[PDB]
Image (cartoon, coloured by chain):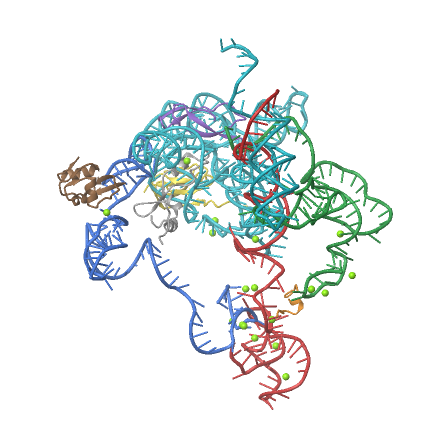
Chain colours: A purple, B orange, C brown, D yellow, F cyan, G red, H green, I blue
Amino acid sequence: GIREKIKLVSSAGTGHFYTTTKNKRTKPEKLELKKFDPVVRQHVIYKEAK
Amino acid sequence: XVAAXXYXVXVXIXXX
Amino acid sequence: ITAEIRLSDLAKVEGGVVDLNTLKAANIIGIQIEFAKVILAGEVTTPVTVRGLRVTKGARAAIEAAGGKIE
Amino acid sequence: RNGRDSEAKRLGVKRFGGESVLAGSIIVRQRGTKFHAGANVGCGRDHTLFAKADGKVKFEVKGPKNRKFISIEAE
Amino acid sequence: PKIKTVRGAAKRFKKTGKGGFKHKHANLRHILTKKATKRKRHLRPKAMVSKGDLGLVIACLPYA
RNA sequence: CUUUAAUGUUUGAUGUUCUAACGUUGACCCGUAAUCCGGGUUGCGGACAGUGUCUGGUGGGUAGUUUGACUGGGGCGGUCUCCUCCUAAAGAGUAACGGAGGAGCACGAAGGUUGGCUAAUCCUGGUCGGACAUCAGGAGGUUAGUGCAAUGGCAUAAGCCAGCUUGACUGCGAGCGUGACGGCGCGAGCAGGUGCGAAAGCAGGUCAUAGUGAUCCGGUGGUUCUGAAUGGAAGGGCCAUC
RNA sequence: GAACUCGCUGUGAAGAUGCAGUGUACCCGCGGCAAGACGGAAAGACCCCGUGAACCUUUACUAUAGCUUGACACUGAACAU
RNA sequence: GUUUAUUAAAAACACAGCACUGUGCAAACACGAAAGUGGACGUAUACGGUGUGACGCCUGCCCGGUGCCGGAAGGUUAAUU
RNA sequence: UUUUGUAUAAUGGGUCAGCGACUUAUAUUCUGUAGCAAGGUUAACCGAAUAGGGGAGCCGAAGGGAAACCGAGUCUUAACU
Ligand SMILES: [Mg+2]
Ligand SMILES: [Mg+2]
Ligand SMILES: [Mg+2]
Ligand SMILES: [Mg+2]
Ligand SMILES: [Mg+2]
Ligand SMILES: [Mg+2]
Ligand SMILES: [Mg+2]
Ligand SMILES: [Mg+2]
Ligand SMILES: [Mg+2]
Ligand SMILES: [Mg+2]
Ligand SMILES: [Mg+2]
Ligand SMILES: [Mg+2]
Ligand SMILES: [Mg+2]
Ligand SMILES: [Mg+2]
Ligand SMILES: [Mg+2]
Ligand SMILES: [Mg+2]
Ligand SMILES: [Mg+2]
Ligand SMILES: [Mg+2]
Ligand SMILES: [Mg+2]
C-alpha cells in the first residue's frame, strides 16, 4: 500500500487527465509535469496530485 | 466385522 | 423505421414517381417505415423521379444517367 | 514445506540456421543476452531477438569474446 | 414451442457479414491505472469469436 | 431598523379538574317461567385503557436453508494464485502430501538522454587508529556491484558519478511468440507533438523474468451519439477513470 | 444358469468339483454328522461417496408468531403553568 | 408405586418434604385470527413455573462473563416533520 | 453385466408362454431429394372445400458502425503509408 492513486489534470482547459501513483508521506509536494494533451494536440503543463 | 451391530437381535432376518 | 431501396426496385412502383407512399403501395418497404434511402444495388434503366428520399452519391449518378431527377 | 513451482515460459530458439523468415519474426526468446544481435536483427526490452528484414538466419561467433551473434542475411 | 434466446448472450455478440460474431474485449472496465497504454489501446477495438467457441455462441443465439 | 416588554395566538408541552366518546367479567328492571345476548336505569372508571395502520427493539417459540475441495480410506495437520531453480532423459512441454527458496511491491528518480568513470580482497608504509574508518603505493582482475528470491545476463557495461530534462508521450501498427478459450507477450515502421546531443542518433518507463482479480451492479469527469406526440430534460451509449 | 457335481500339488480377478499334471474311483439307495459348495435368508446397518434426506442444537445465516416502544386515527371540554 | 405393548424394570421416572420465582383477580398462565373456555364457582395458609428429592448433620468463597431485577444524568438512535 | 482385468468363489436369471424401454408436438440448423428462381412462399380466414381465392406477413437479393449516419463501402483517427 502506502502509494496512492492520483490524477494529473491538464492546464489547457480540456478535461483530459493522466493517472499515476504517489508516495504522500515522503513527497508531499504536488507533482507537475509537461505531458501531451490529445484534445488540443500539444504539450502542456499537467498538475495536481489528487 | 461382516455382519455386526446386532440383525434381528441374533436371529438374522426375522420379520413375519 | 428506416429502410434501404435498391435501384432494381425503382421500376416496380408503377407510376414513375418514387415516394414513401408509392413504395408502400408496391409492397417494397412496409407500413411503419418513415425514412428510406436509395443505394447503388442493381441497375435502373428507366427515367424515374425520386421525391423525398435520401440518395447515395453512387445512386444519384445512376439515376441521372438513366434520365431521372432527384427532388 | 515445498510444493511450489512457476509456469514454464517456453523460452528457446524459434528459427534455426538457414530458415527463411519475414521481418518481425522472433528468432530466440532468452532471459539474458546469451545470443547477441547482429546485422538486421534487433533486441527487445526482454532481450528477445527479432528479424528486421527478410532473409535467412545465420549463427556466428564473433569478437575477442567469441560471443554468439545472430544475423539475417538478406536473400 | 419457439426456441428462446439467451438474452445475456444477445447483449454481448453481434453477427457479421460472413457469419462470424464480434464481441468487446475483457479487462477494460476498472483497475486501469496499473495497465499500460499499449495494452489498453489494443483492447479497445472489437474482436471476432474464436473457432473453438463458435459452437457455444451459436447455440445461445438461434435467431442471430 | 437599534433594541426589545406585554397582549392576542397555528400551535407545543406539563399538570389539575370535568363528562359527553369509550370500558365495566358492580347493582337493579324488562324482553323472559333464561348466570347467553340486547335494551333501559344507576354507580365506578374515563379521553386513560383498548383496537387498526406505520415504526425501533427483542425474538431457536417456529420455519427455510447453508456448513468447500485435494488427500496413498476418512478425520486431524498441511495445501489452494503468481515468480526462480532441480527432478525433466542436450528443441518445447512433462507428475507426486518430491527436493529448495521468494511475491501480493518500490521509484517523479531508482525514468530519458549527453558527457565522464571502474570493482572485491590482500600486502607494505603512514597521527590518534586498533582485525577492519581515512591516505599513498603495489599485487589481483570482477571472486565486486545490480532497490528485493533464484536463474540467465551485464565492461560498448545493464555497475558508479554529473549536467539538462518528462518518451513513465497520443493515435496506429507489417510481422511473430504463447495459450482449449477468456487472454498474455515481443515488435520494426507510419502520423502528430516533445526531451537530450555539435551531429550520426537515442527515448512509447526501470538488466530481464513475480508485485495480481473476469463479468455484473454502481460512482466521477468529458462527449447532443440517443432522447417513447414535439422542444427540452431524466435515463441510456461512447471515451477516460474509481 | 445348465450339470455326466472325486482327492492332492500347482496355476489363475491373487483361497478351484469343473484349468494343468497326477493319484484314486463298478452302478444305485437308506440311517446318521456338519468340514466345503466364499451354503440359504435381507441391493452391508460399519466405512466412504452424492454440491442426497430427515429430525435435533446454538451467541451459523435470513426470516417470522409472540412480547414490547413511539407517531397518527377512534378522541372531547376547562384551567394553571 | 411408574416405564422402553414386541431384546433394557434399573441406580432411570414419580414421590412426601424443601427452596427460588411469578401471580391482587377481568390473576399469572394455557387453548383459541376471535367470541369464549380452563385456572376456579378458587382469592396469596391460593394458584402457576423451575430445580432438589424421606429423615439426621449441614449447605462454604466468587456478581468479572451471560441472564434477570432496579436506576436515571448524559451519549447514540425509528417512523414522523 | 461391470471392469485395468472374470471359469471366476463378483452381479442377474427355476423353466415356458404372453407383455415389457429412444416416442410425440412445436421451433431451429445441416444433409439428401423435388418445385420455382433474384426471387421463393403464404397464415388466419373465405370457399361449389385436398381446387380456387387470400401476399397480412416471413426469408433472400448489402454491408459497416454503440449510435446519429454513411453506403460497395464503412468504422477507427486530427489524418492514415
Ligand atoms: Mg407487405
Ligand atoms: Mg468504462
Ligand atoms: Mg432450525
Ligand atoms: Mg473430500
Ligand atoms: Mg528441455
Ligand atoms: Mg530431450
Ligand atoms: Mg480340493
Ligand atoms: Mg444321505
Ligand atoms: Mg451367504
Ligand atoms: Mg449396497
Ligand atoms: Mg417396588
Ligand atoms: Mg421391551
Ligand atoms: Mg424385560
Ligand atoms: Mg434428582
Ligand atoms: Mg476391481
Ligand atoms: Mg480367463
Ligand atoms: Mg457366477
Ligand atoms: Mg461353483
Ligand atoms: Mg440368483
Name which quarter of the figure residue D41 lies in.
top left
The C terminus of chain C lies in which quarter of the figure?
top left
Residue H35 drawn above or below residue B7 = above
Q: Nearer the viewer, residue F52 or F204?
A: F52
Q: Looking at the picture, does residue G12 appear above or below residue D10?
A: below
Depth check: give the residue in front, D6 or E25: E25
In this orientation, which residue lies closer to the viewer: I8 or B16? Answer: B16
Q: Is residue F139 left or right of residue C22?
A: right
Residue F155, position as x, y percentages in the image: 47, 33
Say left or right for C20 vs D30: left
Residue found at x 45% / y 45% = D10
Say whether residue D2 is visible: no
Q: Position of residue H34 (x, y in %)?
A: 57, 45
Which picture quadrant has residue C34?
Answer: top left
Q: Nearer the viewer, residue I72 or F8?
A: F8
Question: In the picture provided, is F54 more to the left or to the right than I30?
Answer: right
Q: In x, y percent, where is residue E48?
A: 36, 44
Q: Quadrant of the N terminus of chain C?
A: top left
What percent of the width, then of the height, locates residue F133? 62, 25
Counting every numbered tag in the picture gives 0
Q: Residue at x 40, y 43 (%)?
A: D27
> Does the rendering let one see residue E63?
yes
Image height of C69 relative to A38, above or below: below
